[PDB]
Length: 262
Length: 282
Figure (cartoon, each protein chain N blue to C red):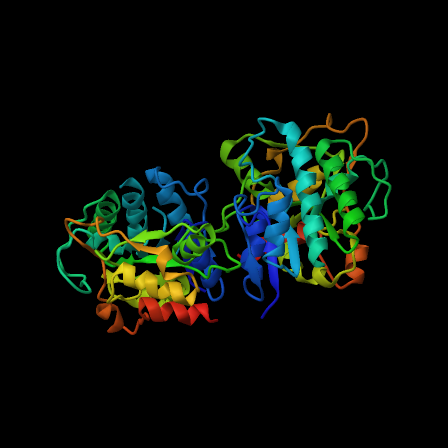
């Protein structure tokens, strides 16, 4: 049985991955205390002692550079969780491809892009997955942060409108479609891959459409057109590179009903 | 679907071992101290109610978050209260609660040999008193609850899963540090491999409510036990030290009699065989 190291096993995506990979794998999910990525040599030792054949990096500079080098001495396969936020500085239209030049405008986008770029340097075999904003079922038994469906529920519950805009093109993904597709990335050649649902409509129309399935009034979803006024934020991904390998994600609205009616 | 199980302290020593073992034939819900704060009665009742575990495995231990032996005197108070709250929540949904007790409840007995679960017990320290006092508050509230008196446990010295410094790791390092490990012949204590504890946990689910000794047996004292385990690991004998000053007045006999547990089909190897077994499988 192949052994897999998952960083941040207590986070949203980490616990789901460990609890899913625990079926047919030996999953080692160290804590922040048990594996602290600010210590170069401790990272080397644990990764050297654990000997994971695959490393899933989900936590959020130094931690990545040190963990990447540790994977590099043992010829390990590292899956880094990147973000669609790398595209937030792009002025183009439509689903973006992985070979387009990106210039993130905020801290989050620049740090994910720079962590992935240092990853390609150290260990070209490592795979970068550009993730979206994710969620589980509002009424899921597994803990989750305050994400999309949950915020639309509290717009109806608190009667406070949810503020979005038509100047953002964003896709949201169900965590399971990411959790149930994660094994396929292990065999993918090293590179950067868009990894999530697709979206052809803007966030106002997208969240308006999801508002009917959850039966919240449409008016509790607001279109603030002053946001992204200067340049619209288009982080809609083109996941066709990932589909040539057999990995498929349903689109934002379809993927939502699929899990919601279950 | 399949039966849903709640494990408290899923990041702790016994919690992680259980979650990764039970995630295989069950749906394991392991909230953090954040999502399952055991200091608030009502989130516990609400959270346990919306979760609906058919089985609740209590690891019963402060996450240390919210303390750091910096007010050791509330640990006793909140740790029975958390068990006290979970007992109501399990009782409110007719759930099966598996409580991790301790063999340290026997540390005040002057008898000799393996001790039984019906023994009159008079724990001498806070932890022995706290588990017995937690045991009795659980049985008051939820008679169906199963209390397992656990021992000091361990994983393989060179295991891939992180663990704190338990026996084998302390003996390896007596050799590395050249500093002897200090034990005594005035303590009769059993240690169990954690895997033999996790792979027997499903059998306790159908077990009638009560208190059960749940671990390895031991007929030898701690000096002889750790010497024999040190020889298997190739630590010299002289790195195991005999402090005759410990428990001089009354010897600490917490060796358990696992006769109740074998009658229900649950079997544990004795301390040294169980160590020799797991040391080799690696």
